[PDB]
Structure formats: C-alpha cells, structure tokens
Picture 1 (cartoon, rainbow over the protein chains, first blue to last red):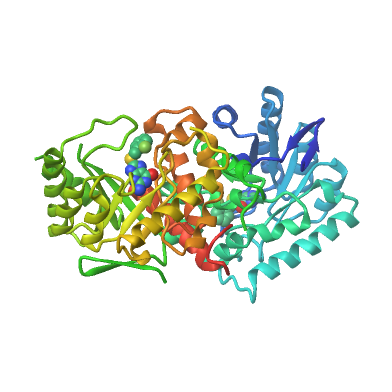
Picture 2 (cartoon, helix red, strand yellow):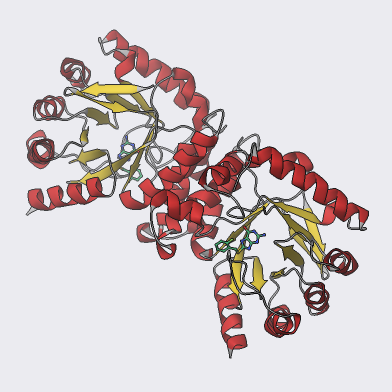
Amino acid sequence: SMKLFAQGTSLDLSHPHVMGILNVTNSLIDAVKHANLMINAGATIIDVGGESTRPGAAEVSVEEELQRVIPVVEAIAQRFEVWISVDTSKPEVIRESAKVGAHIINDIRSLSEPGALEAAAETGLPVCLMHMQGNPKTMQEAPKYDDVFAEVNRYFIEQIARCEQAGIAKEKLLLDPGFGFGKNLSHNYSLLARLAEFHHFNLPLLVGMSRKSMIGQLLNVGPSERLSGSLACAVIAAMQGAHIIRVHDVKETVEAMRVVEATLSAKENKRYE
Amino acid sequence: SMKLFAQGTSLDLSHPHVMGILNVTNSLIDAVKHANLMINAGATIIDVGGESTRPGAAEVSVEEELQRVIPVVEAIAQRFEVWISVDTSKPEVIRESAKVGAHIINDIRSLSEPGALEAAAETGLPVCLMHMQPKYDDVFAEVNRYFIEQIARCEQAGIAKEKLLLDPGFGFGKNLSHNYSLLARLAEFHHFNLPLLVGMSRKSMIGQLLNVGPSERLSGSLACAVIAAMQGAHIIRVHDVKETVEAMRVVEATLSAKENKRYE
Ligand SMILES: Nc1nc2[nH]c(SCc3ccccc3F)nc2c(=O)[nH]1
Ligand SMILES: Nc1nc2[nH]c(SCc3ccccc3F)nc2c(=O)[nH]1
C-alpha cells in the first residue's frame, strides 16, 4: 500500500519500479528518444540529471544545468505518462523542474545546498534523501566508518527530522543508502546485505547500483562488462523489498524484477531478510 | 562447512558453485571444447547428459547412452580438474561413468529404474535426489515429503546421508505457480542439512512469465539463480556460465557481509 503522489498522479509502490537513467551531463532530440526506449522497455520513472555526481566531478553553473535539464523534463512530461525524477541540488532547478512537470526531487546532497530545502518544500513533491559521506570531489579519497550501517541509519534519522521541520511530510520521503557515495567495496556490500533493515522507517527505499564500482572492483572489469553483476545487485535489493531500482539497462532489469515479483507473490512474508 | 568427496578430490560447498550444462544428445572434440569454455568461464562442475531430459525427449538404449556418455566423461576426467555430474537413470551408465571418473550421479528419476539404486550405492559417489511428478494441494509439503522418503530409500540401500544432494526439480511436473512457490520457500529445505541443487536456466517458468523464447531468457535465468543462491543454494545448474558466475560473485560478496550468511 505505499504510494507517492505528485503532479496529480500517483505511483503505486506495492511492487518494485525500474527507474531509467537519463544522463544529460542534437541533445534534446536524443534525450527524448532514449526516454522513449526506456519507457518501452518498462521503466516507470526516468531520472534526468545535468550535473555529474561521479568522484572528482566539476560543478555546473545554474544557467547551464537549467539549459540541460528543464527542456528534457518538459519534453518528457508533455509526451509520455512516465514519472520524472530530477537529479539536482540547485533550488532553481528544483523550482523550475516542478513547474514543467517533474515528480520526484532526487538530490544526492539531500537538500543540503542553501535554499534547496525550502525550494523542495515549496514544490510539495516527493524527495529522495541519499546518504553521501563528504562531497563528490572528496568522497572516494578515503571513505571510513566505524559502522557504516549505523552511520547511514543515523543520517536518515537526522535528515527525516530536518525535512519534517521544514514542513515536508514524512509521507513524501524516500531513502537511498547511496551506493558508491563515500564507500569502499566492503562498505557497499555491508549496506546491500543489511538493506532490509532500513524498512523500519516505513519509507520507500530507492537504490542505484547499476554498472557501479562495487561491481567493477569485485569482477575487475570496466563499465561495459557489468550487466550480470548489475542485475544480481538489483535482484538482491528487490528481494529485500527495495521499491525503486535505478538502472542503465531497463529491459533486462524489468525482466529480472518480474521474476522477483513472481517469487515475492508466492511468499507469505513478501520479503527476504 | 559442507563438503562432498569423489574420485580422490572434494567439493567445498561453503560457497555456491556453478554447474555448466553439457548436452551430448569430433562430436567428442566439440564436447571437450564446450567443457573447456565453461571451465574457463568459472564452472566448477559440468553436467553431462546422454539421454535428453526435455519433456518428451527420445529414450535411448543402454548401448547408445554408453556410447554417447562414457567417452565424454572419460575425456573430461583426463583433461580437467572439474567435477563431472552424469545425468542418467540407467545402472550400467552409473557404473561405467564412475569407472571413468564421474563425481556425481544426477538422476532426474532419483534412481527409480531397476538396479539404479544398487548401482549408485556400489559407486560410493554423491547422488542428487530430484523431485518429479500438474496438481498439488501444497507443493512445498509434497516435495518435502518426497525428500524424506527418498532419503530413507537411499540410507536403507547403504548410501550415507552425507552423499546426498536435494533438488526440488524446477519445471518437472510443475506449473508456473508451483515453481515460484518452491523458489520462494527454497531456504526451508535446509532443515535436511543437505546440499541443495537447482536448475532453472532458460526454463518455462521464465519463458511463460516474461513471454519470451528460449534464447531471450538470460536476465530471468540470472534472477532465478540469484534468488536461489541468496537462500543458500549450493549448486546452480546453468547454460550461461560466465554471466551466472559473475552474479554468484556478487551474491558471495553480499553473503560474506551478512550475519546469517543467507536470506529467508
Ligand atoms: N538517488 C540516486 N541518484 C544517483 N545518481 C547516481 S550517479 C553517480 C555515481 C556515483 C558513484 C558511483 C557511480 C556513479 F555512476 N547514483 C545514484 C544513486 O545510487 N542514487
Ligand atoms: N538435477 C537436475 N537435473 C536436470 N536436468 C534438467 S534438463 C530438463 C529440461 C530442460 C529444458 C526444459 C525442461 C526440462 F525439464 N533439468 C534439471 C534440473 O532442474 N535438475
């Protein structure tokens, strides 16, 4: 019965959804063709991102981010029924994205930028809170935790409170442990192994492992050879009741999720732990 | 901690193993070549079958099955360290397979043919017991009862419980619903304290769910493998070894980080 509400429609999270990655970091036409392919392959959310969130990434000006993101969000919202998430940290991109039809604010920085928290609250949209240690320029230099699960859990307690106190209701929130965002290989797998334990907040869990270093470093291969590992990650997360799976390879992930759904439907508990 | 012993070597079941499918139904050279490819992709067991096990595959005589199966088992045992599973129901093939180096007797009929039970016992080899019957009142309970019965039948014939493996038999007299019920509850079969072997690769339980043909089932096959392996399944029987081994390494990294070392 978990549901999100945005832009006059709803997203029913009684089964896992696949979120397709639309990286915008002729551009507009190609972006829209890619969205269309992902929607046809079964993605029910498209994640539009105009600033690199990779280790070492450089900042993008607000004017450049607006130019990359807003025309894409608008074009998708006008042509398809799919939900649209916006991968942004900037109050102006948040505001302007919501005006042209975006459904979810998916900020790697959990609205930490000046004015972001107020901008998000003003839109009334769902907000995903993600854990990152440090920032993208520093996060992978030397990630360190005494207990990564406890520290991510504590972060979620603190950020939920921060959001509620700004007037964003608990029911609008999603949580994401932020695979690859200030974590070494062992930290990532600790979080994946214990993912179901984050259900105590009674909030949707969003995860993104597709073609990430936690697969590449395990298998010692480049990004192009990570699909089997990516599907394994997706299935592991979805078997533990993760609600949204953020991926590059939509068709394959959707097929894997249908198998997970068939399995969970046969189960009494409806989850693994 | 679980281990099997055969032909002077051992199989460490503390982590999942991928078993590659070698159907043998210059054919010898091609079979060795395919075994080589699967071993280089990380398979640690090869399942050699001489009479196909598909729903209505043609039955073959003992002489034909020996001619097809024994040279392949022999060639692999001479050339590789990999374990060799033989898919047969005939006592003669069980016997002769053991003599040329097979490690596991994998009989879809659970040694129900005349003399098969005795032949298997004489070899001293590990034996896989598979459920095959679609109608059930409670499919898990029916499969669980069958294991209890076959375990006892084996022990009574002098086959130590420690030589046995259990397989719920995905796709063997089971509809879509029954197959997913057994997959959902697979971890409950650990109460026997025996190895669990599963084979879902490219099966109807994927094909019918997704509405795709047999060459378009890789993603669903990998999902099934992962679901089984996260529940502590010990051996995963597959067509697509490279991809399954990669998925199993992710499963292993996850289980190594977990307190339980499995999901239920
Ligand atoms: N919510 C959410 N948004 C995201 N955006 C990115 S991309 C940068 C990236 C970072 C680290 C490793 C590989 C990468 F590709 N990853 C996520 C995620 O896991 N969750
Ligand atoms: N132990 C064990 N041995 C096996 N041999 C086969 S091939 C049959 C087969 C192939 C294709 C479609 C349907 C089928 F029934 N499947 C298994 C298994 O699931 N477990």
